[PDB]
Amino acid sequence: PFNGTMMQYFEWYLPDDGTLWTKVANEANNLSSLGITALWLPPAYKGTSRSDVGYGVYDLYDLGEFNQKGTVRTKYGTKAQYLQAIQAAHAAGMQVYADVVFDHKGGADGTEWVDAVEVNPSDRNQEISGTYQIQAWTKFDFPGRGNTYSSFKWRWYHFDGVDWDESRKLSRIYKFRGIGKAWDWEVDTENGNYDYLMYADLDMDHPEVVTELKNWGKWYVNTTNIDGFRLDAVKHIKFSFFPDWLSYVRSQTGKPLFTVGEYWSYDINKLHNYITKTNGTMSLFDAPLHNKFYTASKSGGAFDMRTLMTNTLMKDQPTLAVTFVDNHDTEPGQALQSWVDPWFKPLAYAFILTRQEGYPGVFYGDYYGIPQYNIPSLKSKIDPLLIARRDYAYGTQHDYLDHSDIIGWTREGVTEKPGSGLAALITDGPGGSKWMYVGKQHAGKVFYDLTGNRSDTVTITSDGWGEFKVNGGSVSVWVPRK
Ligand SMILES: C[C@H]1O[C@H](O[C@H]2[C@H](O)[C@@H](O)[C@@H](O[C@H]3[C@H](O)[C@@H](O)[C@@H](O)O[C@@H]3CO)O[C@@H]2CO)[C@H](O)[C@@H](O)[C@@H]1N[C@H]1C=C(CO)[C@@H](O)[C@H](O)[C@H]1O
Ligand SMILES: C[C@H]1O[C@H](O[C@H]2[C@H](O)[C@@H](O)[C@@H](O[C@H]3[C@H](O)[C@@H](O)[C@@H](O)O[C@@H]3CO)O[C@@H]2CO)[C@H](O)[C@@H](O)[C@@H]1N[C@H]1C=C(CO)[C@@H](O)[C@H](O)[C@H]1O
Ligand SMILES: C[C@H]1O[C@H](O[C@H]2[C@H](O)[C@@H](O)[C@@H](O[C@H]3[C@H](O)[C@@H](O)[C@@H](O)O[C@@H]3CO)O[C@@H]2CO)[C@H](O)[C@@H](O)[C@@H]1N[C@H]1C=C(CO)[C@@H](O)[C@H](O)[C@H]1O
Ligand SMILES: C[C@H]1O[C@H](O[C@H]2[C@H](O)[C@@H](O)[C@@H](O[C@H]3[C@H](O)[C@@H](O)[C@@H](O)O[C@@H]3CO)O[C@@H]2CO)[C@H](O)[C@@H](O)[C@@H]1N[C@H]1C=C(CO)[C@@H](O)[C@H](O)[C@H]1O
Ligand SMILES: C[C@H]1O[C@H](O[C@H]2[C@H](O)[C@@H](O)[C@@H](O[C@H]3[C@H](O)[C@@H](O)[C@@H](O)O[C@@H]3CO)O[C@@H]2CO)[C@H](O)[C@@H](O)[C@@H]1N[C@H]1C=C(CO)[C@@H](O)[C@H](O)[C@H]1O
Ligand SMILES: C[C@H]1O[C@H](O[C@H]2[C@H](O)[C@@H](O)[C@@H](O[C@H]3[C@H](O)[C@@H](O)[C@@H](O)O[C@@H]3CO)O[C@@H]2CO)[C@H](O)[C@@H](O)[C@@H]1N[C@H]1C=C(CO)[C@@H](O)[C@H](O)[C@H]1O
Ligand SMILES: [Ca+2]
Ligand SMILES: [Ca+2]
Ligand SMILES: [Ca+2]
Ligand SMILES: [Ca+2]
Image 1: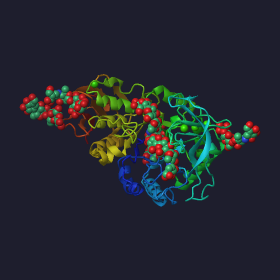
Image 2: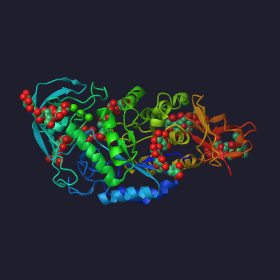
Image 3: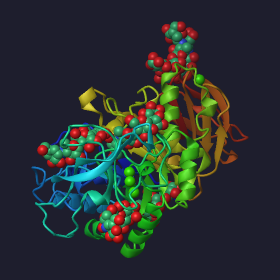
Image 4: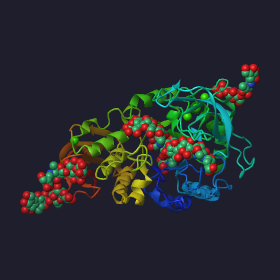
């Protein structure tokens, strides 16, 4: 038995110093000893510039190897350093998930003239202009790479649209004209059709494009030996595309390739729609649960903690849910900003780390800190919870989400891991106590608070129950002493 634990190993405001790949190589041992079993690494290919975080993808085939966009290395380092990081992660017994950005392409080498029409930004099925010629950033020739690995050249007809006309300096949503040219479907229905997002938007209906992304998928897994994918911005990408893409790349590389997609919506039914449409071929980030943590942390104690799990992927589809507290898009200043307050953050990590539903992740920004906004590191509060997950969070779970402030759950432990077992309490309000069942196999044992928030102890009764306790606005994780 084991508890998988992933770590997203970057944040937005990292300096553009080309050191992240080296840091993975240096830290892989430490993180593994804490029970981290997988790293989600940022996009490793060349962006619109060297300080691009990776989501403005210029060349999928340039892993910090070719002189392109004014730099050889990416933000994170060179191609050689990227490979060493992956091998170090493997030597320490960790999987590696690579960020995959297929929705769009930016930083084109040149413009092309294209017949286009404006569509309504709030309803992309509604044309709001006539057809006219625009100058669109869609020519990709890759002067620094040549035909190495791939001789495919991208042009306007491989895309469905852009949001910038270079001749008139106009910013509108332009749909391209052409035989069969249309926004892709199925996609998210916010704004009527949410296929267009930014830069030059890929046409997943074009067979040349499907083929090229399949060839890149195979090439990339074989070049890097990565173990899986984090799929960026999947709600803006033809739903049927990734079932077909993943089954090609998995079977043509001989690898299972665990895959988590980022479907950003707090509407659980949209996530359920996407899982059924893609036949459960991938996990998804539990964005609704993130929204729960953010809301509870801002509600001054008035959140009903009995609803913390309701309408989350961790409640509804736990084996396809990847759980988290914050990520690079929820950071201060970002477009999805909804930063979980530091007082509540240890409570949210305890919830995803010591419970049996879902595949939890630790955020780099939470672990190491975000100096850009003077947010201090929470490593000293997260590490006890990882040790809880590594050693104690095993076996039958009993739920007590039964009070509007104080909620808890227990894990009984497993014979295969002697000394396992835990009882966790969190509260968004004043402290208190709660009786919970850990199992009569623990009768007489003394439990202590692994987080060190409390100095007292709890003795288990002859019937397997303990009256566990928590401070106000705090976490306690009670585990057996030895
Ligand atoms: C390091 C670890 O890699 C493998 O485990 C990974 C799984 O193959 C993935 O599928 C994924 O599992 C998650 C599920 O997809 C998901 O539905 C959810 O329910 O949570 C799961 C994770 O909690 O991620 C896993 C890694 O995080 C591989 O199977 C495993 O063998 C590898 N490590 C084990 C190796 C040994 C066996 O002797 C022991 O050290 C431990 O049991 C494991 O650490
Ligand atoms: C001039 C530039 O225009 C295009 O790039 C723009 C995008 O199309 C816009 O959508 C917008 O992107 C922002 C995102 O929407 C936003 O969500 C944020 O997260 O990231 C972006 C921040 O700006 O803005 C983009 C730039 O204005 C076009 O795709 C792009 O390729 C064009 N860049 C060319 C211009 C120069 C100067 O000659 C060259 O350095 C580039 O290599 C060219 O590619
Ligand atoms: C007009 C001329 O352009 C054609 O080139 C591109 C199409 O215009 C694009 O729309 C695009 O087609 C893809 C769709 O966007 C996509 O939704 C999916 O259906 O796959 C399509 C590609 O398989 O990409 C095309 C190029 O890759 C095309 O090269 C060419 O056949 C077209 N020439 C026609 C001109 C007239 C117009 O009446 C007709 O008389 C001729 O029979 C056509 O040859
Ligand atoms: C730039 C940003 O645009 C998209 O995000 C939009 C959402 O999809 C909309 O539904 C809405 O987002 C949420 C609200 O912000 C939030 O208040 C929430 O309570 O409700 C809405 C969803 O329930 O507004 C957003 C428009 O600004 C897009 O999905 C998101 O991914 C984009 N930000 C990233 C763009 C890339 C894609 O390559 C990411 O990888 C980058 O990290 C970000 O720049
Ligand atoms: C009433 C009782 O609650 C105290 O504070 C906890 C809150 O219940 C939680 O909601 C949370 O407070 C955070 C806010 O939600 C957030 O908006 C932000 O302001 O940060 C707050 C945390 O820093 O966490 C609180 C625990 O730190 C706490 O359990 C307890 O001390 C409170 N009773 C005190 C109230 C006053 C005067 O009546 C204090 O001087 C006394 O120590 C207690 O009587
Ligand atoms: C003599 C004194 O010791 C005991 O105090 C323990 C209490 O169980 C808690 O205070 C316990 O948890 C605290 C955390 O360790 C600490 O980190 C803090 O941040 O919050 C928790 C408090 O909620 O730590 C103590 C160590 O065992 C005992 O229970 C306490 O009753 C004992 N008597 C004192 C209590 C009062 C209050 O009216 C005074 O009048 C007495 O004179 C004290 O002697
Ligand atoms: Ca299309
Ligand atoms: Ca799209
Ligand atoms: Ca499209
Ligand atoms: Ca409450």
